[PDB]
Image (spheres, coloured by chain):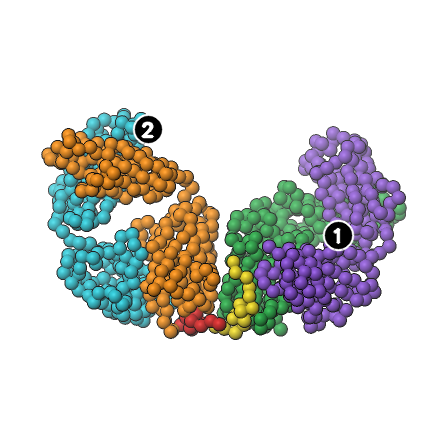
Chain colours: A purple, B cyan, C orange, D green, E red, F yellow
Amino acid sequence: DIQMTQSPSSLSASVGDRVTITCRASQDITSYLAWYQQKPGRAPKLLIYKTSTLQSGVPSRFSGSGSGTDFTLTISSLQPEDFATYYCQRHDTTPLTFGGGTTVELKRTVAAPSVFIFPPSDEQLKSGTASVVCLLNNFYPREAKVQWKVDNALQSGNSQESVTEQDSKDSTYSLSSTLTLSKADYEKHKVYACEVTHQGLSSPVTKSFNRG
Amino acid sequence: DIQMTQSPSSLSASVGDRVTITCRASQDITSYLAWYQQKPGRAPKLLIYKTSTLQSGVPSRFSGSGSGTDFTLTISSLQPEDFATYYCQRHDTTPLTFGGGTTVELKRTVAAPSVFIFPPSDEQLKSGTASVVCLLNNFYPREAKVQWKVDNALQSGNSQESVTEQDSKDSTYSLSSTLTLSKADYEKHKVYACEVTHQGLSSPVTKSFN
Amino acid sequence: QVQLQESGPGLVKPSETLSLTCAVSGDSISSGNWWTWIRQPPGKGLEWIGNIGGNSGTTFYNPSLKSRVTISRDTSKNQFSLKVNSVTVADTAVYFCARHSSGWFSLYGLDSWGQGVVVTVSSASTKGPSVFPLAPSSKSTSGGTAALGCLVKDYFPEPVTVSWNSGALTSGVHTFPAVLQSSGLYSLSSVVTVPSSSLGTQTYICNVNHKPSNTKVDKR
Amino acid sequence: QVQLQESGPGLVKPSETLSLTCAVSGDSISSGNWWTWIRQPPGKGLEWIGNIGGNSGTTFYNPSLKSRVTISRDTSKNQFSLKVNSVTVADTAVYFCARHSSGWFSLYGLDSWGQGVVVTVSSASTKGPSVFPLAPSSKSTSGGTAALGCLVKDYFPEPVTVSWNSGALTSGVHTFPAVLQSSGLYSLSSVVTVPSSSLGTQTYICNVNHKPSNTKVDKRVEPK
Amino acid sequence: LQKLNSWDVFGNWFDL
Amino acid sequence: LQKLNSWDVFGNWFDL
């Protein structure tokens, strides 16, 4: 029923900046709103209840505000251990819906990706499948576009892709794009290419190989 | 996991006869047992609780007795409306298991059954099925054995029978058994017999057609 | 002055979830009474399924079914509910909802019941009955009298009502219990014994009514 | 002062009944707290399922699931349970159980959570992982750095742990999340960046462990 | 835990 | 389908 939206869906800021997240409902809920912090793969941590009442043990730099259908979670002097996903929750009457969530990054210098392509293995080919893997190592920001061209044929719906979280040290990401085919289709073509477009690339970077 | 049992599973007595049904529990339940009366097709009627506390509005002739793992429901001067199935229930701790139930009859003169046999109709024959019906009308006691014989061939598993209640007027029973076969297996044979064995028959009685 | 009323689907399929409701009037759900659910398969005794405290909120079930049963309560609508998940064919029964009255520290008995609600579990669909006459013969004429009837066969689900000549004929009729055949459908027979001379002046017609299919048949 | 711990099957089949339990220590089940069940699909946000009062016994559910959900409680064992009947594949997620603190007339927040429990709904059977080498070459050489890896494909259920050189190599490794292929089987890749000179001198082996099937495999990764 | 005890009946008899 | 109200948050606070 109730609809809780958070904004921005994700933002990036450096340590020391004053950060602010917004959470809006679809109907009045007085001063009953709860904020949570969630580290990767971990359970949430109750930060705030009753709009701005800070849970015991939470740092002072966390502050809540707002009333009705427009709430605000502000972090003064953002710290490294604050990069996480933040959710809001209606806590007055059912169905105590959670917001969409807001992820917080660590803004960093733009780093172009290192592009690597791997042809299918001989063991896998013996098994009837061909998986061409394309890698993009350590790159910031997270927005990167990968394309698959087989004999200059734009591909679609035959590839899966997976990305990692911010590396704890260099605050860069890494992307993997595996193109899976039948050993028949794979051997029916010559040149396979992995074209990348990223903010740190003045022109698209292709990493291709011939089947022969 | 109490395993409550009742005895007798069924009995017959006429108006005026005092009756005594027993209920047994595999473990002790102090004096916490409840008795219910259930008419055919009606929800039970709470009769007794606390081993012998009569529910308000229940006739005085209903009485309870016992303790621990043995109890007794006694009906002095049984009345006509007291025909029913009676259950005992543990009502102190889970799972409040019900008993198996005891049915009460109305004894009456041992009447012989009016045995009829009905062949399949012209319509059902057009439908490709052959259901031969054998009727037993107004008889007593309720026990009756019916066996189908297609050309001296006893049947088993391919026929079903259903019995009626004690008619509210003459306290007799009625049984209907239907043997259903494909019209192929039917028209092949020519003689079909319905064998009835009953307490009032020295030897089985056969009723057949062509 | 208590009054309970069952409601819910009279037919579910195997493996689906069965849900039934019991409205209460004349008393409050939030009270010391333990509201109970009872089922009785066709042709068998009573089986205690489970109860729930109107105020404590705690539930108790039959150990043979605790994994599939769920009882709830609704204080506003004066109702309580039952849910039987992953239902099987062997669950066809009449489901009663009753009020298990309570003393100060011990329980009494179920002094208020509902008329019940029939709920069949089968994969078959609704079907109208095929009516066939069961005519008399030399074997169905014990000197005097003459027995006839109608074989209402191949229909689903129960029940079916049968009347003779619009209900005018009533003496000597015996309608037998329907049998659930291996085909999943039902079939019964309704006979009536009458004088053999009545065949020449009176007419005999059986009127079958199977409302689940909105069917009305008449077959001499 | 309060610690919750989930427990139950981490794998159920579609249409079956899921049963989970949450043990509580340091406080009483029968109290003014509202014991709540939360779930979060892989890579998605939180979804409040339902809660239950320790003493009132009444329950509240998500209107999009009230028909399939059932919350219960067990005072003696300091536990409360959740049952999800007629499950579907789209219910695979991490199921949290938390304590929804309450005031006199105003709820508060979920201040104590359990670590969570992963539960998958899938028809596929437990299938050990196939490991294939992603060998370094001139194609996977940008600058003086060379990249290699291992392709862990066609396996079920999650998870799989991948180390390099028997846990000796940890710098520069990037193991990617697994994607559930149309075949109902997962698939991931674990790569490692090393100086181009190391290819001719050093040996590299990825160690995969998939205990759901008691599978332990090691794969050398060699050029050409 | 089958339980069901007289005190649970007492609890089922009182509510706020 | 009633909604949680302050009385439900109080009645369950100390009871049974």
- In which quarter of the view is residue A194 placed? top right
On screen, D53 above or below C82? Answer: below
Chain of the residue under label 2 = B
Q: Which residue is mark 2?
A: B127
Q: Nearer the viewer, residue A139 or E13?
A: E13
Q: Is residue C115 left or right of residue D27?
A: left
Which mark is nearer the camera, 1 or 2? Answer: 2
Point 64% across, 65% down: residue:
A30
Question: Element type at marker 1?
Answer: loop
Q: Which residue is mark 1?
A: A164
Give coordinates of residue A111: x percent, y percent. Answer: 86, 51
Q: Is residue A52 left or right of residue F11?
A: right
User: CB under 8 Å between callouts 1 and 2?
Assistant: no
Q: Nearer the viewer, residue C198 or A116?
A: C198
Q: Is residue C63 left or right of residue D180?
A: left
Question: Element type at marker 2?
Answer: loop
On screen, A196 above or below B51? Answer: above
Give coordinates of residue A26: x percent, y percent. Answer: 65, 56
The amino acid on which the numbered mark 1 sits, given as a three-letter code, is Thr
Q: CA distance from mark 1 to mark 2?
A: 70 Å
Chain of the residue under label 1 = A
Tag 2: Cα neighbours inside 10 Å, few (<14), some, or many (≥20)?
Answer: few
Quadrant in the picture for the N terminus of chain C: bottom left
Q: Nearer the viewer, residue A135 or C7?
A: C7
The amino acid on which the numbered mark 2 sits, given as a three-letter code, is Ser
On screen, A108 above or below B160? Answer: below
Give coordinates of residue C113: x percent, y percent. Answer: 34, 59
Point 71% across, 32% down: residue:
A185
Tag 1: Cα neighbours inside 10 Å, few (<14), some, or many (≥20)?
Answer: some
Is residue B19 in sight in this rendering? Answer: yes
